[PDB]
Length: 114
Image (cartoon, rainbow, N blue to C red; front, side):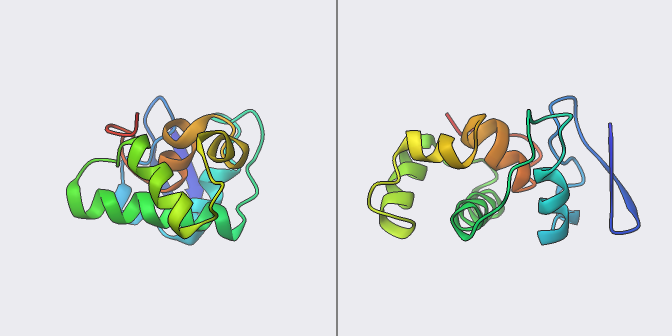
């Protein structure tokens, strides 16, 4: 379906992932985060959320896939907080790094992030 943000109508897939992925910015991230068609509840983006979002998006821009969860957790422990395990990632992103975090980070698919 569509997502109205910033005077634009962006294309999402059936799982709520941004298909016009190159149109993404912080504003789009925010609209995705409150998109309750694809999330039980809006997700309030803290700086921790943002650190995770920026990491996923940089990885996709560089490698064309999302990083594996194994690598995400390692990164989070090093750059977010020493106790940021997968459970902590689900605390931030209730549906997980693929269904929530990669979606909000504007990746066109979460492929790789398992």
